[PDB]
Image (spheres, coloured by chain):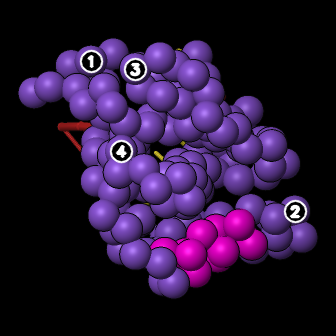
Chain colours: A purple, B red, C yellow
Amino acid sequence: EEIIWESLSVDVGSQGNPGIVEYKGVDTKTGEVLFEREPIPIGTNNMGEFLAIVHGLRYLKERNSRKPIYSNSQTAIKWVKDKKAKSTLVRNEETALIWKLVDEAEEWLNTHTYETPILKWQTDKWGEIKADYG
RNA sequence: UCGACA
DNA sequence: ATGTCG
Ligand SMILES: [Mg+2]
Ligand SMILES: [Mg+2]
């Protein structure tokens, strides 16, 4: 039913899938951009959606913030709950970068605790997530 | 069937 | 329109 305005919204942006991946986190209320990751030459949508949520967890934890995080990605929300990113992306020299980030994010989740609620953004009811690249 | 990314 | 990540 209602939107928690006091929250962080994250989203992935890509050119191709697999292709160039970036992601960002914004204040759900204002759209202020709080963080934006530099483009990764090759990655998948779901790897970027996963990295964006874990980045968000780290970002809120470091700031002593209890805000929830919104993502529109059912996949990535589950990966974070599992502490495991089940991506099909081949491992090679070109995908080394994003696979290192993904392994590091998983290791962060295995070494830290959080109470942050990770919430599904209801695109069908509320329109595009406010972190959308549009 | 559904959630995304193009 | 057609394609890929889940
Ligand atoms: Mg998304
Ligand atoms: Mg989007």
What chain letter is assigned to the residue under label 1? A
Q: In the image, are marks 3 and 1 on the same chain? A: yes
Give the residue type that dot 2 points to: Glu
* Nearer-N-terminus badge (4/3): 3
Q: Secondary structure at mark 3?
A: loop
Residue A18, how many percent across, how many down? 69, 48
Relative placement, left or right, of A18 versus A49 is right
Label 4 close to label 1 by CB (< 8 Å): no
Mark 1: few, some, or many residues within 10 Å (few <14, many ≥20)? few
Give the residue type that dot 1 points to: Trp
* Nearer-N-terminus badge (3/1): 3
Say which residue label 4 marks.
A67
**How far apart are the two marked residues, 4 and 3, measured between alpha carbons?**
12 Å
Magenta span: predominant SS is helix
Q: Which residues are magenta?
A: A100-109
Image point 50% across, 69% down: which residue?
Answer: A85
What chain letter is assigned to the residue under label 4? A
Q: Secondary structure at mark 1?
A: helix
Residue A44, how many percent across, how many down? 63, 51
**How far apart are the two marked residues, 4 and 2, measured between alpha carbons?**
35 Å
Give the residue type that dot 4 points to: Lys
Say which residue label 1 marks.
A126
